[PDB]
Amino acid sequence: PHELESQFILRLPPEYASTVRRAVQSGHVNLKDRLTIELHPDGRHGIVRVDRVPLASKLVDLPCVMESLKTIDKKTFYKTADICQMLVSTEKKFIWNHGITLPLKNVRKRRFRKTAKKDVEKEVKRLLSTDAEAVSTRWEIIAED
Amino acid sequence: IIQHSIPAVELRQPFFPTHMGPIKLRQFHRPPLKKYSFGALSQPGPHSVQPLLKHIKKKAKMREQERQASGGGEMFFMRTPQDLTGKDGDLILAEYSEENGPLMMQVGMATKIKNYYKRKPGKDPGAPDCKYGETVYCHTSPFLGSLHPGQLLQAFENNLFRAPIYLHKMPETDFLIIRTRQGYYIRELVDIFVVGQQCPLFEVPGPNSKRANTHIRDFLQVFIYRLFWKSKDRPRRIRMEDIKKAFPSHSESSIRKRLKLCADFKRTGMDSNWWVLKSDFRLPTEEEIRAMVSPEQCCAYYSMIAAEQRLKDAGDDEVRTAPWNTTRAFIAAMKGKCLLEVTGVADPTGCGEGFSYVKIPNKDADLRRLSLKNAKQLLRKFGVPEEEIKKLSRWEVIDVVRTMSTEQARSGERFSVAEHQERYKEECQRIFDLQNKVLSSTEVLSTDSATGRCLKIYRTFRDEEGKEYVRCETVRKPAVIDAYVRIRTTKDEEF
């Protein structure tokens, strides 16, 4: 079978980004030893090791949706993957408010129409299980108390 | 004119899914980073990324050899799923301004970049040249606004939408990591476009529509035909629970309706518990199966069911922002049926930038007995200018006095065409110009219930050995409240 490739964006500190960029544009396999990525079983934490120097990483959710588009003639472009995550290196914390481009900054706060967390469904599933495992249940809409 | 990849026009499941559940509809076009169970990345630890530069230039040299061996013209290369990897070719990135667009391309589909260039009045030097796309000279603006003289605007153009794009350079810190089961791979990116508000060219169907049910039936039929083509046994035969694995929300009556014509069930003997193909039935060829369902219809269906999920999760303003309504409104506005309020609640920005695609409609005897002279004195009394009094044309003077009128009404116990159309046209251009300026800006931007009643639930459980403790739990979140009590009210009516 075929599994859709999973592309994400890696953001590095600027000096480490310059060393990684120089090693990528060089093209040797020396970069392969120099740059490693360890993703922790949290799923939202990691180390990126540039030249064997550890950097602390967080995999965050991006507010917009990006799409990689490949081409052979620079006139027709074929969509290859959807990018929604970024492993910035240096829950609410794992959500990035800004977009990658310069015009998109504070997009989630200003350029996004109010949208719901769809979280609440999981919380309702937790309450329903407790109700069904009880004997009696007493609902009461309340006032200030 | 748009030629998608052979995985896209054949509707392969990895790229075009048969069924999307609720957690996969909430993560629509935002696929999370999945953990592998088997493979090299499934083992926990540090993993080296691998630089592909030799792979990119080897594949590009190989494709140029293929093109020059085939006569040197333009070729079609995307024939396999392995052609659609990010490991080769010139990648650009494309960011979207809206959170959830009305239409969005699946993986494997093609789009074109058109550079619309309105010439200057009289002499013009020529289109400012651009790295990507082909240039076309547009007298009639494709978008809602109109291009300025000497303004080049790039745009994504395909069968799904048409949207203005703006080339920005990438950040100096960001690279692109393509992870697969075997390892990590790294590219740099240099070009990233920002895609403005889409102008939809395909109408998303509504839920339970006739077009919606027709697409569901045709998609199931195409999947059944392609399973029959993949079958190796001579009287081609399939299994029902393959289709039940692909379409699990379908009632099996509908699947048996699709299999009733073109197949029959063998219970005993050879081919037992298989749906063999009927001997008189000619299985359709590849081009007929491609003519059954189009990929853009699948994208419109995916947009409909994703919007169905988002609306369902969020408990009439939201219903107007649903893509079937907005796509119908925009396509009707493009034929000239109706106009759109460009400021409204369907605005995907939430501020004054961007448009909203929701429909608005495009919409006494004695005066003659005045005997010219007294009508002249009346026109003098009302304050009519002396030119109209001076011509003194009986019929014109009476018509002007009738136009002056005096109104009045009470009981007891005015352009409707040009002005309305002109205001809509100017506002569309103003919003379009504002959207272009905000997205183009390389300027850095500084980082920045009704009842008032909570819900309390008391209960009764039995502890180990013998006990009867009661727990009183108070829910102060109005969101948890609504979902909780909605289910309770539904249950009160399930019996």
Image (cartoon, coloured by chain):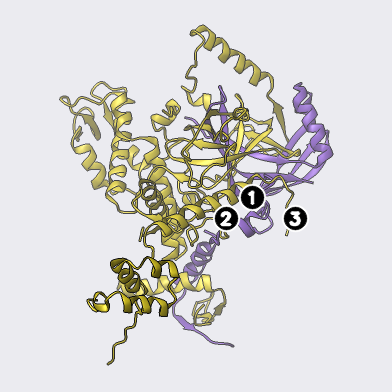
Tell me: residue B198, above or below residue B447.
above
Q: Position of residue B178 (x, y in %)?
A: 63, 33
Query: Residue beneath label 2, please?
Result: B353
Residue A61 seen in this snapshot:
yes
Extreme left residue here? B280
Q: Quadrant of the N terminus of chain B?
A: top left
Colour applied to chain B: yellow
Mark whose residue sits in front, 2 or 3: 2
Q: Residues within 10 Å of mark 3 (few under 14, many from 20)?
A: few
Query: Residue beneath label 1, please?
Result: B438
Do callouts 1 and 2 mark residues in contact (Cβ within 8 Å)?
A: yes
Q: Which kind of residue does numbered mark 2 sit on?
A: Glu
Do callouts 2 and 3 mark residues in contact (Cβ within 8 Å)?
A: no
Residue B301 picture quarter: top left
Mark 3 / mark 1, whichever is N-terminal: 1
> What kind of element bears circle 3?
loop
The numbered mark 1 sits on a residue in which chain?
B
Q: Residues within 10 Å of mark 2 (few under 14, many from 20)?
A: many
Q: Is residue A17 left or right of residue B273?
A: right
Seen from the viewer's position, the closer of residues B286 and B389 is B389
Q: Is disc 3 on the same chain as disc 2?
A: yes
